[PDB]
Amino acid sequence: GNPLVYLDVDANGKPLGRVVLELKADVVPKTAENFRALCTGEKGFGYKGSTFHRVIPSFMCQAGDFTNHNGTGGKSIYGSRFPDENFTLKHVGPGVLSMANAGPNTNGSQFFICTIKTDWLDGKHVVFGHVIEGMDVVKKIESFGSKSGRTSKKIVITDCGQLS
Ligand SMILES: O=C(NCc1ccc2c(c1)[C@H]1C[C@@H](N2)[C@H](O)CO1)N[C@H](C(=O)N1CCCN1c1ccccc1Br)c1ccccc1
């Protein structure tokens, strides 16, 4: 089966709700497993406590840099980086879950949730899941962003984990 995971997100201490994500282990098992483990923190590090450091309305909300907290860092459960698994899943619309990178084969822990169809990223960013529930939460996060990516409130993953 495919993992169901969750992120509980707050803005300046105040809760915004939960985002439930399906991880497509059936298509990208290595990428799904990385994200899953980072949600439970079972390796001793993960997304808990880290921020949505970059939010661009009508594009995406980006998170996952739990080492540098500014978009330069993050790491995977396999090491500092791992290859692009495949590009089978596409950026088809809002709610798509996909990996940030710094060029080919530089996946770590940073990721983003699309708020529109970002199909110009097809073949360059590995899509590995989608929002099952809580798109309204994602819209709340989005509303605190700006075209520059800076947020007007600190958007934090207070908790995360696995539902099944
Ligand atoms: O934020 C990053 N890169 C930082 C990063 C990402 C991953 C890792 C590391 C560092 C570290 C640690 C580990 N992994 C490896 O060791 C490598 O070094 N990349 C942007 C991006 O991916 N997207 C997707 C959603 C936002 N974004 C985006 C795309 C197109 C247009 C505008 C934007 Br805005 C970008 C920005 C601009 C162009 C291309 C990519």
Image (cartoon, rainbow, N blue to C red):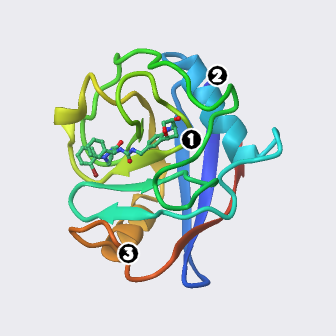
- Looking at the picture, which amino acid does disc 1 mark? Ser
How far is the residue under mark 3 from the one under mark 1? 20 Å
* Amino acid type assigned to the residue bearing label 3 in the image: Thr
Lower position in the chain sequence, tag 3 or tag 1: 1
Report whether the residue tagged 1 is closer than 8 Å to ligand 1. Answer: yes
Q: Residues within 10 Å of mark 1 (few under 14, many from 20)?
A: many
Camera-near label (3 vs 2) is 3
> Where is residue 128 drawn, in percent x and y?
46, 30
Determine whether label 3 and label 2 are within 8 Å by CB. no
Q: Which residue is mark 3?
A: 151
Which residue is the site of mark 2?
1
Other-residue count near label 3 (Cα within 10 Å), few / some / many at <14 / 14–19 / ≥20: many
Residue placed most toward the observer, 18 or 58: 58
Rendered view: 54 above or below 27: below
* Residue at position x 54%, y 48% in the image: 73
> Is the residue 160 above or below the residue 103 in the image?
below
Image quarter in which the C terminus is found = top right
Q: CA distance from mark 2 to mark 1?
A: 22 Å
Residue 3 lies left or right of residue 130; in this view the side is: right
Q: Position of residue 36 (x, y in %)?
A: 66, 37
* In this rendering, position of residue 127 left or right of residue 161: left
If the image is split into quadrants, where does the N terminus sit?
top right
Mark 2 and mark 1 lie on one chain; the one further toward the N terminus is 2
Residue 164 in sight: no
* Badge 2 element: loop
